Length: 121
Length: 121
Length: 121
Length: 121
Image 1 (cartoon, rainbow over the protein chains, first blue to last red):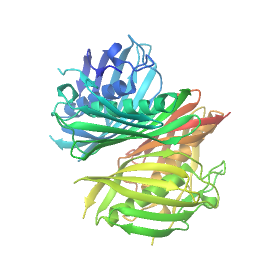
Image 2: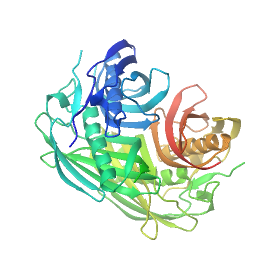
Image 3: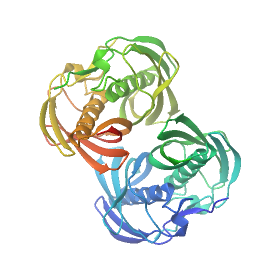
Image 4: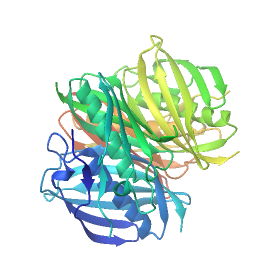
């Protein structure tokens, strides 16, 4: 047995403009995996949501086609995670977003790149 | 504003044996994104959890180093998703897991590959 | 100093039809890296070329948007590599190709997934 | 029929120091694909070679475990490509390298992330 893995039970949107987004969130029990670390799916979901927010901030609608994520350092209970996303490439049908998560000590937690398909304006 | 994104509010483990895992789950409202489709992070978390289950089934402990996911077809409210994970490569220090999600119509929803780091036995 | 890294100085196309491609090639000196193993770029290029051939076999033109590759086992001088590609998903604007390389002993060398953008028919 | 795809028929190492590498190269006919653009495999090989150079610059020996690449803008015959590699994370067992290619106009051509396995020192 294991409990649900949840993301964004709390959050603060610090910045959302012109393809650049910054959101903060506190790691809580529902964020964790078996080993007491922030779940890789939780961390990914933080990144994917912020990637979507980057899309919206460009006046676009979109869907993720593909994503790659690298895990660098564990997130822990009560960490404050800063999720920074930006559009590195704005093409006609597709956008590429980089999203980076750091903890309250400025340490790198994970980095992801999203390939989004622009569906409309 | 947006509500939390959650994964495994419900599930059934069908198979978990020697590097092969099958788990089913039903898509619910907490699974969805802005547009009413299964959230990319939700789908990834389904895959990531099953990847870790594959690791455990091998009598191993481990952590995800890197993952890539491709989104093929939308997941919808009330879909039953089958999450199939396989260890396609068991190295000494790392394992590589393929995870595929199909819906109740047999349609491919997404595919991911996980690069896991074996921490212990 | 280092010499050029080259791919397809020799090859045999065994199969090319309906989204399924099989090509063989022999690892030669220009294939190798500093350590005497098949260069990761060489192996990737084998996969990317076969992904393109899968596109053509579907009566399409296309360009790669994104690719992810996992390296499983070293390729060595004089290995015969079998490169098998297939379209796992044929969407309207994009295709997803899986490409797998095995050696003459049937051992898995590397696996890659390509997200291609369909440019025309 | 198609001719071999080659990388580093010419190059200039501009910088190679403590985890940071810059290398330039000019796109030639052997660099290109069917459509006359820089081959995705050629571009990846440029990135992969520079990733390994980053590893060496850290006094390390290593092998690529996994890589992801995004293609942003076509490379063309006679372009001068600048290949910039950085170790963004030096773990104990693995390193993560970001590699970016820009052309002579400062335009972003592609970006890749490499997950390297440290074999020795």
